[PDB]
Length: 465
Ligand code: HEM
Ligand SMILES: COC(=O)[C@H](c1ccccc1Cl)N1CCc2sccc2C1
Image (cartoon, rainbow, N blue to C red):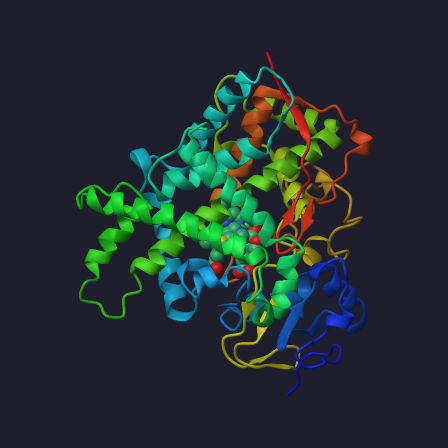
């Protein structure tokens, strides 16, 4: 059988000359033009099948679910994970860690409170914090990280850190600093000639160093956990894992050991922080470009929720407008423009092609979220893409900002609760304003890579009465 169509590789250099100085995403989309929806390109000596549009991705990730369930690797961070922890595990280790990982976020945690209740509490702390700024213009970057972290922290490390605590301000810097270097221009060069480049200095050193410094903190918290553990009454994620360590003393094939634990907390502690939060950032940037929409969300909050009780997650179903606005921030925000890389698990017959076992597959989620076949005028913000005549919420197949399939975002339910409660709680209590007029807000990312990062912007949060 055949590999999909695509340009001709100079070996060692692969397809360097058919790429584009813009980035990995521009490059793939510029080839989509020539070779179709499924196609093959050469990053270094490595072949990758590339998937485009709703229909291609869905065929692969959902119709050949298991076939496409394997994970690839981000060269810039594989020094750190090396096939360990939940994001980057594969086969049995992955199955095991995902399974445990779903179960554990749903139930055991700080104050034995529900994830909702916890996100509620964080939101309550964001409000009090924001009030303190008295409407002065800030940059919302830092607070937006603080609040997403503290959720993940409260789950994994069983506690939340105070916004000014310098132990914690330093984890946030590392995390933000890395996630931006991760998706800088250099780290994409690196995605191509990792083999050659991993010798000379560069941006991957910095990322490695930064990540190792988080592992240190993760490490020294596992230890406190283990010391002061209690079998009767597991505090949180780490505590539960340790008890599963004990349950598994006599299983030689148990995957619950110190590497996976450390690197699972790193994955969670990463994703938990750096996406749910840049989404919020982008979301508020859009609200500054579209005060009309913000007034409608704010009226909808006034009707369904009112101005005294805090927002609750069951309100979402009663608030389709807001729910559309959030959908539409995820779609246009589009913070993972070409998925996290997959690999096929067996030899696979795809659109009458053979994709050999272990060949890397890039589901380009951004070309689904901007897919003209499913969204009109797909580069413009419109909450209407998710509403019908009657103002009811309206599902759309092109909408997969969390990927699809067997590898679908595990955090999805937390992400969605954080989005809904954080935007409705801020918007219930504050009115927003920037110096920049709506007509000159630019939505062009400060970095477009393996993830998208919105530009910095000023914003002010005015207490409503
Ligand atoms: C709105 C914010 C988020 C977005 C847009 C998002 C999106 C994604 C995407 C696109 C993937 C790749 C799925 C794939 O290619 O198979 C993924 C994987 C993953 N995400 Fe999320 N995510 C978000 C929030 C979170 C949160 C809050 C957590 C923390 C619990 C999280 C944890 C994970 C994990 C553990 C994986 C790996 C799943 C696996 O490999 O089995 N994500 N996410
Ligand atoms: C690839 O761009 C990201 O936004 C990711 C991401 C977010 C959510 C789910 C999975 C992923 Cl990989 N992060 C956050 C977690 C980690 S671990 C090493 C690097 C990154 C960058």
